[PDB]
Length: 183
Length: 12
Ligand SMILES: [Cl-]
View (tube, each protein chain N blue to C red):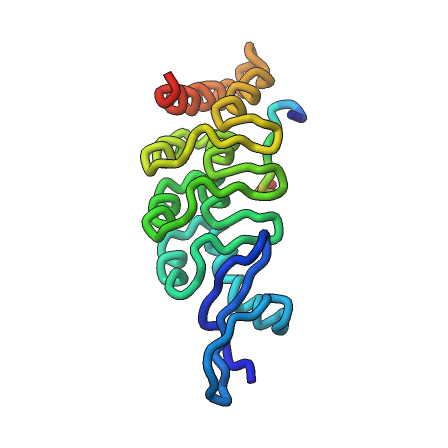
Protein backbone atom coordinates (compact mmCIF):
# COMPACT_ATOMS: atom_id res chain seq x y z
CA UNK A 1 0.00 0.00 0.00
CA UNK A 2 2.97 2.39 -0.01
CA UNK A 3 2.70 4.34 -3.25
CA UNK A 4 5.06 7.26 -2.45
CA UNK A 5 6.33 9.82 0.06
CA UNK A 6 4.48 13.07 -0.56
CA UNK A 7 5.75 15.06 2.43
CA UNK A 8 8.05 15.17 5.46
CA UNK A 9 8.57 16.62 8.88
CA UNK A 10 11.15 16.20 11.67
CA UNK A 11 10.28 14.36 14.92
CA UNK A 12 11.89 14.39 18.43
CA UNK A 13 15.51 14.91 17.39
CA UNK A 14 17.51 13.74 14.34
CA UNK A 15 14.54 11.65 13.22
CA UNK A 16 12.33 12.12 10.15
CA UNK A 17 8.62 11.35 9.81
CA UNK A 18 7.00 11.09 6.34
CA UNK A 19 3.61 11.72 4.78
CA UNK A 20 2.36 8.68 2.90
CA UNK A 21 0.26 8.54 -0.25
CA UNK A 22 -1.33 5.08 -0.41
CA UNK A 23 -2.22 3.52 -3.81
CA UNK A 24 -5.19 1.46 -2.58
CA UNK A 25 -6.92 4.82 -2.07
CA UNK A 26 -7.25 5.63 1.68
CA UNK A 27 -6.17 8.80 3.52
CA UNK A 28 -2.53 10.02 3.60
CA UNK A 29 -0.66 9.00 6.83
CA UNK A 30 2.48 10.16 8.70
CA UNK A 31 5.02 7.41 9.42
CA UNK A 32 8.34 7.07 11.26
CA UNK A 33 11.06 6.91 8.65
CA UNK A 34 12.16 3.50 9.88
CA UNK A 35 8.70 1.97 9.09
CA UNK A 36 9.20 2.24 5.37
CA UNK A 37 11.78 0.69 3.07
CA UNK A 38 15.26 2.22 3.09
CA UNK A 39 15.58 2.78 -0.67
CA UNK A 40 12.21 4.55 -0.75
CA UNK A 41 13.42 6.96 1.92
CA UNK A 42 16.80 7.24 0.17
CA UNK A 43 15.42 8.30 -3.25
CA UNK A 44 13.41 10.95 -1.41
CA UNK A 45 16.23 12.40 0.74
CA UNK A 46 19.22 11.89 -1.53
CA UNK A 47 18.39 14.74 -3.85
CA UNK A 48 18.12 17.16 -0.86
CA UNK A 49 21.38 16.18 0.86
CA UNK A 50 23.16 16.14 -2.52
CA UNK A 51 21.98 19.69 -3.36
CA UNK A 52 22.78 20.92 0.16
CA UNK A 53 26.42 19.85 -0.26
CA UNK A 54 26.82 21.26 -3.77
CA UNK A 55 25.14 24.40 -2.41
CA UNK A 56 22.94 24.24 -5.51
CA UNK A 57 20.61 27.24 -5.43
CA UNK A 58 17.83 26.08 -7.79
CA UNK A 59 17.67 22.34 -6.99
CA UNK A 60 16.89 23.29 -3.40
CA UNK A 61 14.30 25.69 -4.83
CA UNK A 62 12.12 23.03 -6.49
CA UNK A 63 12.72 20.36 -3.86
CA UNK A 64 11.18 22.64 -1.31
CA UNK A 65 7.50 22.08 -1.83
CA UNK A 66 5.98 19.49 0.57
CA UNK A 67 9.31 18.75 2.25
CA UNK A 68 10.21 20.14 5.71
CA UNK A 69 12.82 22.86 5.17
CA UNK A 70 14.66 21.91 8.36
CA UNK A 71 14.79 18.24 7.52
CA UNK A 72 17.59 16.88 9.77
CA UNK A 73 20.18 14.18 9.11
CA UNK A 74 21.41 11.74 11.74
CA UNK A 75 23.65 14.33 13.38
CA UNK A 76 20.91 16.90 13.63
CA UNK A 77 22.23 19.10 10.79
CA UNK A 78 19.81 20.76 8.37
CA UNK A 79 20.56 22.04 4.89
CA UNK A 80 20.98 25.49 6.43
CA UNK A 81 24.05 24.28 8.37
CA UNK A 82 25.72 22.72 5.29
CA UNK A 83 25.15 25.79 3.14
CA UNK A 84 26.29 28.28 5.81
CA UNK A 85 29.40 26.03 6.03
CA UNK A 86 30.00 26.30 2.29
CA UNK A 87 29.52 30.06 2.10
CA UNK A 88 26.48 30.19 -0.12
CA UNK A 89 25.09 33.58 0.67
CA UNK A 90 22.29 32.54 -1.72
CA UNK A 91 21.30 29.13 -0.38
CA UNK A 92 21.24 30.77 2.99
CA UNK A 93 18.90 33.53 1.85
CA UNK A 94 16.79 31.05 -0.09
CA UNK A 95 16.33 28.65 2.87
CA UNK A 96 15.85 31.69 5.08
CA UNK A 97 12.93 32.89 2.94
CA UNK A 98 11.43 29.37 2.91
CA UNK A 99 11.19 29.56 6.75
CA UNK A 100 14.27 27.63 8.02
CA UNK A 101 15.02 27.93 11.79
CA UNK A 102 18.05 30.23 11.94
CA UNK A 103 18.89 29.27 15.51
CA UNK A 104 18.95 25.52 14.83
CA UNK A 105 21.52 23.60 16.86
CA UNK A 106 22.92 20.32 15.56
CA UNK A 107 23.50 17.51 18.01
CA UNK A 108 27.18 16.55 17.45
CA UNK A 109 28.29 19.74 19.31
CA UNK A 110 25.36 22.16 19.57
CA UNK A 111 26.56 24.14 16.55
CA UNK A 112 24.39 26.49 14.47
CA UNK A 113 24.52 28.16 11.13
CA UNK A 114 26.57 31.00 12.66
CA UNK A 115 29.08 28.68 14.28
CA UNK A 116 29.61 27.11 10.86
CA UNK A 117 29.89 30.39 8.93
CA UNK A 118 32.37 31.47 11.65
CA UNK A 119 34.19 28.15 11.81
CA UNK A 120 34.76 27.76 8.07
CA UNK A 121 35.35 31.52 8.03
CA UNK A 122 32.46 32.75 5.92
CA UNK A 123 32.19 36.49 6.52
CA UNK A 124 29.48 37.17 3.85
CA UNK A 125 27.26 34.47 5.29
CA UNK A 126 27.82 35.64 8.88
CA UNK A 127 26.63 39.08 7.62
CA UNK A 128 23.53 37.54 5.99
CA UNK A 129 22.71 35.53 9.14
CA UNK A 130 22.96 38.49 11.51
CA UNK A 131 20.96 40.54 8.97
CA UNK A 132 18.24 37.84 8.56
CA UNK A 133 17.94 37.89 12.34
CA UNK A 134 19.78 34.90 13.72
CA UNK A 135 20.35 35.03 17.53
CA UNK A 136 24.09 35.69 17.96
CA UNK A 137 24.02 34.79 21.68
CA UNK A 138 23.21 31.09 21.10
CA UNK A 139 25.84 28.84 22.61
CA UNK A 140 27.33 25.55 21.49
CA UNK A 141 27.74 22.58 23.83
CA UNK A 142 31.01 24.07 25.14
CA UNK A 143 29.21 27.34 26.12
CA UNK A 144 31.00 29.15 23.25
CA UNK A 145 29.00 31.59 21.17
CA UNK A 146 29.74 32.09 17.48
CA UNK A 147 31.85 35.13 18.31
CA UNK A 148 33.83 33.46 21.09
CA UNK A 149 34.59 30.63 18.67
CA UNK A 150 36.05 32.98 16.05
CA UNK A 151 38.22 34.46 18.84
CA UNK A 152 39.24 30.95 19.92
CA UNK A 153 40.17 29.74 16.40
CA UNK A 154 41.98 32.99 15.64
CA UNK A 155 44.22 32.66 18.70
CA UNK A 156 45.48 29.26 17.49
CA UNK A 157 46.28 30.26 13.91
CA UNK A 158 50.10 30.79 13.53
CA UNK A 159 50.58 34.61 13.63
CA UNK A 160 53.83 35.41 11.72
CA UNK A 161 53.13 32.82 9.07
CA UNK A 162 52.79 33.84 5.38
CA UNK A 163 50.63 30.74 4.55
CA UNK A 164 47.69 30.97 7.04
CA UNK A 165 47.75 34.76 6.68
CA UNK A 166 44.67 34.56 4.45
CA UNK A 167 42.37 33.11 7.09
CA UNK A 168 43.65 35.80 9.45
CA UNK A 169 41.95 38.68 7.57
CA UNK A 170 39.03 36.30 7.24
CA UNK A 171 38.52 35.62 10.94
CA UNK A 172 38.94 39.29 11.70
CA UNK A 173 36.02 40.27 9.44
CA UNK A 174 33.79 37.60 10.97
CA UNK A 175 34.65 39.16 14.34
CA UNK A 176 34.01 42.70 12.99
CA UNK A 177 30.55 41.67 11.88
CA UNK A 178 29.50 39.91 15.11
CA UNK A 179 31.04 42.47 17.55
CA UNK A 180 29.04 45.22 15.84
CA UNK A 181 26.05 43.41 17.34
CA UNK A 182 27.27 43.18 20.92
CA UNK A 183 29.08 46.49 21.34
CA UNK B 1 40.82 22.92 18.95
CA UNK B 2 43.25 20.52 17.18
CA UNK B 3 45.31 23.52 15.86
CA UNK B 4 43.28 25.81 13.57
CA UNK B 5 41.46 22.63 12.35
CA UNK B 6 37.65 22.77 12.05
CA UNK B 7 35.63 20.45 9.80
CA UNK B 8 32.69 19.26 11.81
CA UNK B 9 30.88 18.71 8.50
CA UNK B 10 33.38 16.44 6.72
CA UNK B 11 34.29 18.49 3.65
CA UNK B 12 37.83 16.95 3.40
CL1 LIG C 1 31.56 34.23 2.94
